[PDB]
Image (cartoon, rainbow over all chains, first blue to last red; front, side):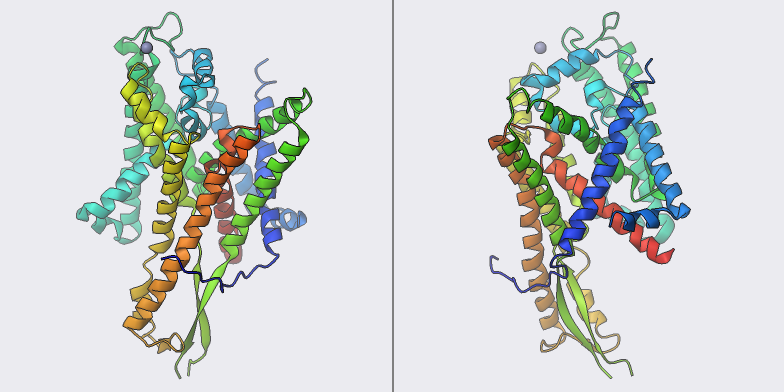
Length: 46
Length: 415
Ligand SMILES: [Zn+2]
């Protein structure tokens, strides 16, 4: 069907912001962890 | 906020599990430079950069960039996902396997070991299939000089590929037991996000030359964050259906209906599925009929993107929607007299919950379909282009993150 149940709890109204803050932290962490994993294998070449 | 992680990580119990998780992905990244005996990686890279070998995008993404340089895990942990989907179809259709499925602790780990032996065998095939149909294909198009289309190569790739997959699949299941979150999940996740930092770096080096402007780029990074947010908003979002219990032991509660039940799996699933056509059809270079087949499902092109987006919908809906929901819930309310206020107990409860879950779950799916489709549009109007930030790129990254963070607290409650 295509009817709306808009009245739904979004138990986070602006805890969304801290959720997003958690996700962006997780990725950017690993991102830099795994980003250097490249150069750490570069100075291991010679 | 940044320290809310710090202290909760400064407890050595988990700090050890992170330093193992990171270590296993380190050795996985180490293997990425272990080239397959007879393969000319410079030719492979050249090919992947041409328009012809463009379709291999998603394949090289979920390989973690291993295909790009035929490592011992050329395809990565992806053959294992293929086995996971095969055996979880056969668990449904074939009933004898359904018996073993529902058969408790050790019974659930036997299917797990028929899938584990499913995957490793599937690596042998895929390795051979590529060595035969693609790698030594034309003049040994991608063979280093000295190497030849003989069975010596065939066998030596099959070995490199079974060695690589076995190594890796073992590495996977350690990240589950002795590490954070889920192995496989985190492996896929690693493949995508590795290629992020240099990309982000190279994009701002080319903003300087005058090729890119900071208006478009700042729009793109804004959107990634926006996307990251919307999904975070949606995961948190619930609809509470009020219950109430009879007289002691008589008070009110709520049964929560989420928009998307931990949608980590249907997404990696859908991705795998979409690659099946590409993987079989594309490595036949000279065959036009097959190149059509493969180029149809290419997720960059609108045809493939549409096939991709219909897939993420379906896989998400069927995942979230089927969590042995309505009919048991309606009956279980019998245990100690429970009811949804105002709504008749029994059939009308079933049809009530059914309706709600149906109409809800659907919005959950549709949303995830925008997250798949939109990046391309956004990528197209922008000069920036990469499969790593291609929605399916995002949805798994965001996916594994949440899956991993959620699994911390469930045991961090216990610990
Ligand atoms: Zn040819």
